[PDB]
């Protein structure tokens, strides 16, 4: 029966359309923004973790450089 085929497509269509319209419902908008803000923050803390690890490395390395110069006078 054809009306059973049509009804099925009709129902799928409203569903799809409603899914498409859902992206710009206010609640969806906010959750999308919350999601993106959350991923951002995750990354910001990780960038910052790295920044500080590298800065620490710098100071270690700068001290290793001081050691070497000092070592140089104190063998002389």
Image: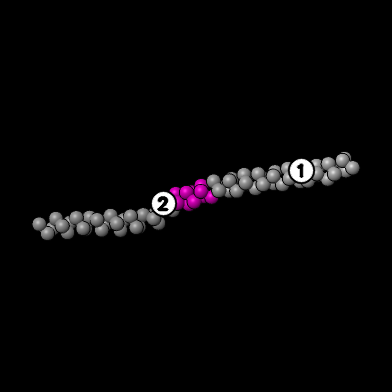
Question: Residue 65: percent from the left, percent from the top?
Answer: 78, 46
In magenta segment, residue 31: yes
Q: Could you tell whether 52 is left or right of 64 in the image?
A: left
Q: Nearer the viewer, residue 4 or 25?
A: 4
Q: Nearer the viewer, residue 62 or 46?
A: 62
Quadrant for the C terminus in the image: top right
Q: Could you tell whether 33 is left or right of 46 in the image?
A: left
Number of the front mark, 2 or 1: 1
| Residue 59 seen | no
Q: Could you tell whether 42 is left or right of 65 in the image?
A: left
Q: Name, please, the residue furthest toward the right.
A: 76
Q: Could you tell whether 10 is left or right of 50 in the image?
A: left
Look at mark 1 in the image and give the residue it sits on.
64
| Residue 74 seen | yes
Question: Residue 49: percent from the left, percent from the top?
Answer: 62, 44
Circle 1: element type: helix
Dots 2, 1 in contact, CB < 8 A: no
Q: Residues within 10 Å of mark 2 (few under 14, many from 20)?
A: few
Q: Residues within 10 Å of mark 1 (few under 14, many from 20)?
A: few
Q: Residue at x 54, y 46 (%)?
A: 42
Look at mark 2 in the image and give the residue it sits on.
28
Question: Residue 57: percent from the left, percent from the top?
Answer: 69, 44
Question: Residue 28: percent from the left, percent from the top?
Answer: 41, 51
Q: Name, please, the residue furthest toward the front.
A: 76
Q: CA distance from mark 2 to mark 1?
A: 54 Å
* Range drawn in magenta: 30-40
Q: Earlier in the sequence, mark 2 or mark 1?
A: 2
């Amino acid at each position: 029966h054809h009306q059973k085929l049509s009804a099925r497509l009709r129902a799928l269509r409203q569903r799809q359309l409603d899914r498409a319209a859902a992206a710009v419902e206010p609640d969806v908008v906010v959750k999308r923004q919350e999601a993106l803000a959350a991923a951002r923050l995750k990354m910001q803390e990780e960038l910052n973790a790295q920044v500080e690890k590298h800065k620490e490395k710098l100071k270690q390395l700068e001290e290793e450089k001081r050691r070497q110069k000092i070592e140089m006078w104190d063998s002389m």
